[PDB]
Image (cartoon, protein in one colour):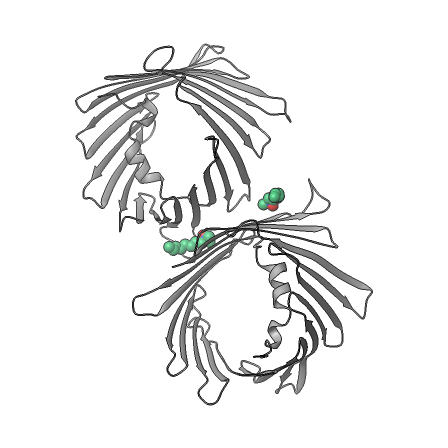
Length: 283
Length: 283
């Protein structure tokens, strides 16, 4: 089953080291409940410490594995309504067809897209069509993989402006507990990442970024240490001397609390320091 | 055991209806852990949504029931250090002696007090002495109780200014699931409260406040409904049309999450609305 990850998921494990475990400047509550009928609910809510912009949301998910059907309804505090229809492994295998819609009964605006995915051995393909105010826009991504090596191309195109708006390449290589990933976005932005699971308890990642049109280089070191099986500690630092720390505790299987802090170097009296609270409830 | 509550606790059950279950404008984390050695830890931390003033704290508590000894150490983010010593039921019974101290290694300031309590049938007494910059200040409270009826007097006195700074009376009456409380503070502020446990699930409270020097009257209605044994819902409204709502869920015995909101009447585009998150962890 050498079925590659989709282009968007290349370098995921390293990104997850750098990004989850943290939640600076926000307080977050995510609740996944389940009714007797089998339809499940997700209610998210987040608040910025500065803007005081509270966002709320409810999602309702209904499944029918027999037809490969997922039906999702979405509500948020912007009064925006969403509806998603997934049809997997029916028109063919393994082909996934998706219809996504959004509508806002205040501003009248209405948007939609048709997503398509095709998973197989050595090949993971995708083609989306976004219908909006300046539509349509065609997205296409392709990833081939054989024996650890990975090769991907991502592309987007405004049909109206007759203009290519995305042109990205990716080369990857995994040897199990070690991932290497590189990308070239628009012939301008160059990126690289390295994931390494050194021990049972220690995970480690490294970020690199550079662009022509400058001698500008940004890079980062990240790590995640699994104290016991119910507690975890993340830490990271970049070349701007921003130090991130995070600590996540599963109080009970299903309930995760997360504390995070961002500390600027060097500072005491004058620095942009941030805190973060995150709570995940799974019932 | 008709041992009355202390003056500060008169009307507690009604106050608890009105006040806990809510946490407007704050996010709060309280953690009560316990070491093998028997010494217990409390770490609190709260953050205002506006001022962005994060406060942190650690308290360490060591006991020795055999001598009636409680020894508490306190640390906070203001770098203020605290130390409390409790000696109960030793000099006599039931007499409690308390030494409280605080010191700030930044501003050099240092404060302390000697608290004394005397519990008995029909009588609950208290006398504190605060040593500060303008010290000392003597506090005294007395509550007598017989067959539901309650009578209390509270008093404070600056010995330096030779000035009485507190003169309060209280009359109460309880008939089990019904409490009535009234107070006269400084001959100016008049207050009253009524608690009523109507059902197993429904608790109810009413607040009243008036002062001479005005025709100013403020009052409030409060209620707490026990949905199931692990969930609870609070609501309240005053005469300024401020509507409070709160919902607390014990996810597991020991873990309580609390959501609260304050809604102004009448408003949509222009009103001071507040949210609140509170989390209690007991391990």
